[PDB]
Length: 138
Length: 137
Image 1 (cartoon, each protein chain N blue to C red):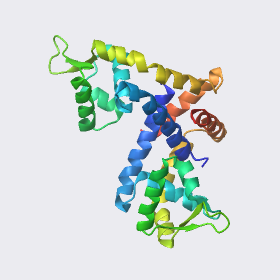
Image 2 (image 1 turned 120 degrees about the vertical axis):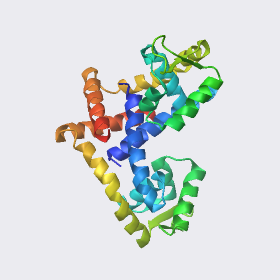
Image 3 (image 1 turned 90 degrees about the horizontal axis):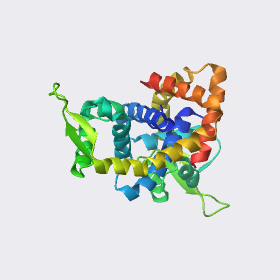
């Protein structure tokens, strides 16, 4: 009960739960919310289908379907850099951007309720330790 | 670097490593954690509702999970004598041996985590972590 195994699986369960409840209104799933967000935030980088797979820690076929779903809703688009052409870069369409800007608040609200329990430099030290722990599990 | 990322991700690495190694026992990650709680907190008696609160999986679901484990003969269920409304859960010897068999997966993991923070930092961390879990609930 005081185990990190317990702690961690619950702090994320409770988190997944609250996000799904809210995203029901956008017709997107937890994973897709996170995918769109990643595309919104770190998009200009040129990330491909593999890059999202790495970022989501999801099996190629999983993430392949996920992207294929969003593309069906035309919320993302495939684009290719001019000289580098066997790469296929993923980007947000104008509707996807509107969507991200609408739920994004869900996450930010949550993030805040989290960081608001610890002190100013108590959050810096905490994040440093999670990154270290998450690194241990690699 | 966002918490949500980290908490999501950490949990992910954990379910995945668990799921791989538990495949050989014909149980799921959730059932694994349940048997653990029963095994762990067993000198005391654990109720169907305590399991429900523990996961905290939906009402029908927990009864459904339990019925499976009991069909697997890993647990017995019976109805408290004082209070007709809660029912009690108990590990079978089969169940006890099974947990003892798989616990090594979860421990090896739980350990390499405490490993990462110096013993003073660990206590501090379980405290902050509990504080955070309190808010989301």
